[PDB]
Amino acid sequence: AASLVGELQALDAEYQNLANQEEARFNEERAQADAARQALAQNEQVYNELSQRAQRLQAEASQYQELASKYEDALKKLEAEMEQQKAVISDFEKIQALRAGNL
């Protein structure tokens, strides 16, 4: 077991580092999802109030017409941000159901 002893130690090292990297990835992913939930929650609040504000502006008849349309665009984007944020949370929850499930 000349080189066998050495290789076994080489594979051990690789394993230790690999285990640590995966643990670092999972944490990096957890932090990002928490950021996602915090941000998403705040956006829901801003989207609701702003969509309400835009709705009132439209129901009138050009300034109101221009500002209403400007809000519909801003809201379209904010909505994309929120779908994107829900995906981060959703992807992490899926991953969680695994890393914790596999026993």
Image: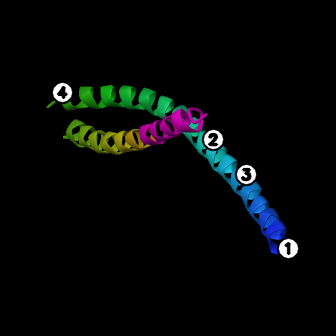
Disc 1 marks a residue whose amino acid type is Ala
State the mark number for residue 20.
Answer: 3
What secondary structure is found at the residue carrying circle 4?
Answer: loop
Q: Would residue 65 appear left or right of 77 to someone viewing this image?
A: left
| Viewer-side residue, 41 vs 2 | 2
Residue at image point 48% right, 34% down: 40
Question: Does label 4 or label 1 sit earlier along the sequence?
Answer: 1
Disc 2 to disc 4, how far (Cα)?
42 Å
In x, y percent, where is residue 11?
74, 63
Q: Quadrant of the C terminus?
A: top right
What secondary structure is found at the residue carrying circle 2?
Answer: helix
56 in magenta: no
Q: Which residue is mark 4?
A: 59
Q: Which residue is mark 2?
A: 31
Residue at image point 23% right, 36% down: 64
Question: Does label 4 or label 3 sit earlier along the sequence?
Answer: 3
The quarter of the displayed image where residue 99 is located: top right
Q: Quadrant of the N terminus?
A: bottom right
Disc 2 marks a residue whose amino acid type is Ala
